[PDB]
Image 1 (cartoon, rainbow over the protein chains, first blue to last red):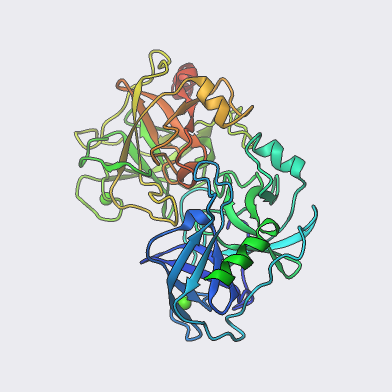
Image 2 (cartoon, protein in one colour; image 1 turned 135 degrees about the vertical axis):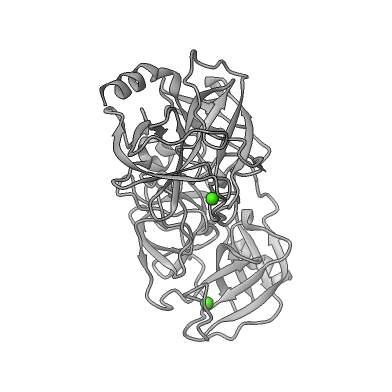
Length: 223
Length: 223
Ligand SMILES: [Ca+2]
Ligand SMILES: [Ca+2]
C-alpha cells in the first residue's frame, strides 16, 4: 500500500499471510479453520501465518499452519479475474485470541460512500520496489459503480467493486493481493486487481464478497 | 520483467540504473554525458550507475556519476503520463567502452510487428514481490495501435505505443520503469505504464520516442 500508515500492533487480528518460502498474498480468517483469499493467489503448497505484525521477525504471538485443502471458485476466470475468490482449509484449528481473531461475512452489500480499511504487506513505493516489514493500513471509501466503470471501461462485472481515490496517490498494490477490505465490521472485498502503486491516482478493483456468502457457507459445510 | 530471461553479462551496454539509496528506475545512455528516462522517475538527487549486471555486487566494470541537471519534458502530464520523457546531464563524461556504450535515436517510427528488447531490474513475480540482482531481458513485438486502445480505452495518445503480449504471462513491471526498449538498433520506447506484473496478459504502454528526436537534440545543444 502506498500513501498509507503503519497499522497499530495487532489492530487487524483477522489478517493472515500466505507464504510459500516468501510472503506473496494476504487473506482473512473467517473461522478457526478456514481462510478466504483471492483465487489468483493459488499455489499447490501454502503455509498460513497468523498473528503477525513484523513479517520478518518472530514476535512470539504467531501461529503457522499448513493448508490441508485449497478450493478455488469453480467459475474463476484467469483472464478477467472474474469470481476471483478462493477458500483455504487449515490442517489444524488455530487458537483464537486477541492477536488472532476472525471477521464477519457481509449481511448485505455495502452502499457507495461506505468507509473501509485495507491492510497488507504489499509494495509501498510509486517508483521502485519496497516490501515493508510492518503491516500497512489505508482508509478508503467505496466509489459508485459509475466511477468504477470510468477508470476500467467495459471491464467491470457484477462481482467486482471499486474502492480508492482518483487523486492523492494512495492505493493498494501487489503484495496486498488477496488481503481483506473491512467496512462496518464486515468483510466486503478482497484485493483483486488495479493499476496499483504505479498509478496511485486511480481506484482499485476488489471482489464483491456479498455475492458469495451462500457459496462460502455451503463449501465450509461439505468439506 | 515477468516470464523473461537473465540477459547475457553486459549484452545491454546502454542500460543504466537510477539510484537514490536504492534502485528505482532504469534509463538509457545516449552520449557520454546524457541519459534518457521517464519523467515520472524524476527525483531531486539521482546517481546514475553504469556498466552493471549484478546490481547488488561490485563486478569491476562499473561507473557511478551524479546528475548535474535533470530536465523533464515541459508538457509532462502526471495524470495521464503523456509526454513521459526526461533527460539527465551527468556531472562528468563517462568513459565509454565495451561494458558502457550508447544507443541510437530513431531515424523513423517503428511499424507494428517489429521485434524489440526490453531490459530492467524490475519486479519478476505476478504474485508477491521480487527484485532480481541480474538484469532481466524480454523480447516482445510492437503492437498495432488498435490492440492498445482495446486494453486501455480512451487513454492512448499519439505519444504512446504498445509493446507486449495478450497472453503468455510476460510483461514489464515496476522497477523496469524508464527502462530502454530497443528495436532495430534504435531506442523506440521508454517503459512508462501499464498493468505490469499483476496482469501480465496485457500489453504495456511506452513513450513513443520517435516523436521527440528534435526536442532531445535542441535540449542537448542548449545545455
Ligand atoms: Ca512475525
Ligand atoms: Ca554491480
